[PDB]
Image: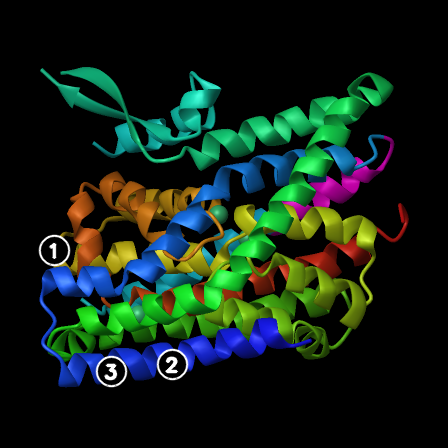
Amino acid sequence: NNWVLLSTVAAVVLGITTGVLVREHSNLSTLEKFYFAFPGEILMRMLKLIILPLIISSMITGVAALDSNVSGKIGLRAVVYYFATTLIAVILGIVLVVSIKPGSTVDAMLDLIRNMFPENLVQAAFQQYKTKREEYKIVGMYSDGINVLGLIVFALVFGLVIGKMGEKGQILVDFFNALSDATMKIVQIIMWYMPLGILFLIAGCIIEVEDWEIFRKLGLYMATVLTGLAIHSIVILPLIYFIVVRKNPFRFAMGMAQALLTALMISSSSATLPVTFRCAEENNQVDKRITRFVLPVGATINMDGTALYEAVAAVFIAQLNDLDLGIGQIITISITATSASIGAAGVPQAGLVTMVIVLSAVGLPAEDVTLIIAVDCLLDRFRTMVNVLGDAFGTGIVEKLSKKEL
Ligand SMILES: [Hg+2]
Ligand code: NA
Ligand code: NA
Ligand code: NA
């Protein structure tokens, strides 16, 4: 049945209708606005709850599944596609934001390498490492926030080891195969509550807006992000698919319409993963051998929409703060945005938590994420669509390159 998609679409229209009517005909205070958004807050807790189980077991399962003999090349072909498309999205975003103009870096760069290799695996599950220079001597502290970057590196390295251990490591492959299946089943349970949670998430965001003048202030910023997301989705990604796979890229995209439409409502690449599998494997007839690796791994590692949005958002905030941006500052933004997209989880608002790392890399407060938080719900919806579209296209791109091994 179509209840999953029809109900989710009905949640979005009811959230906008609920949010606009409540905003106009009611005078909710700050506390009442927070309580009104509570049902959507609980959905965020449910989605953040499965972030760690899903990311860890997805990375281990995908890499471990790849047969060591030759499927490793299939894995390498994917990471090159993931990195190339994210760089293109980041570069495209910086060009658009710099052209349109809508509005201590070493320590931050070194913190990205430190977080790739956490000192503790349990601590990396809910804490991150930050260094500051004080007197100058570097002082490091562990602050809250799951270190997704460190877990990804270990989970991929762990998946590589157990996959290559043959029968000695089969129990670990069986363990994380079942764990990955269980996490996806739990995500399906959360989809029963998502229509209600999404209703108050969209409604709550609209109610928070005060006078609609900020939307006018942020209108050009949204155009830059929406223009970049449109260019990457409609021009760049189809162009890459056509070159590698001499097939109509837009016919391939039509087969993903349910997944793309699902992502445009729930704003979660991990939550829409089951739809991406169904669309890629059945509508597009992509091999399940490579789909079972590209999609679950790319649901969090390949985020072109987030990477573009992080670069545009960071440069836009810098423009607002009247902060000059040299070639060096632009380059660190590109690196930080690329890592921020990797560290972002396939959940609504993931892009905001990782933007603090991008803002700090150029010396900006972590509280400047509230200069663009008003319209994040809309821009987050389109981020996810491009994030999952990248994985879907990469699924067909990797399959073409892996004809010899399949
Ligand atoms: Hg919103
Ligand atoms: Na990418
Ligand atoms: Na993705
Ligand atoms: Na990510």
Q: Which residue is label 3 attached to?
A: 20
Residue at 62% across / 31% down in the picture?
Answer: 156
Q: Is there CB contact under 8 Å for labels 2 and 3?
A: no
Which residue is more in the foreground, 328 or 74? 74
Q: Which residues are magenta?
A: 69-81
Residue 298: % across, % down? 60, 50
- Crowding near the residue tagged with mark 3, few <14, some 14–19, many ≥20 C-alpha atoms within 10 Å: some
Residue 161, numbered label: none
Left or right for 270, reference 326:
right
Q: Which residue is label 2 attached to?
A: 14
Q: Is residue 85 visible?
A: no
Residue 321: % across, % down? 11, 55
Work out which quarter of the rendered image holds the N terminus and state it: bottom right
Q: Quadrant of residue 221?
A: bottom left
Identify residue type, mark 1.
Asn
Left or right for 131, reference 152:
left
Predominant secondary structure in magenta? Answer: helix
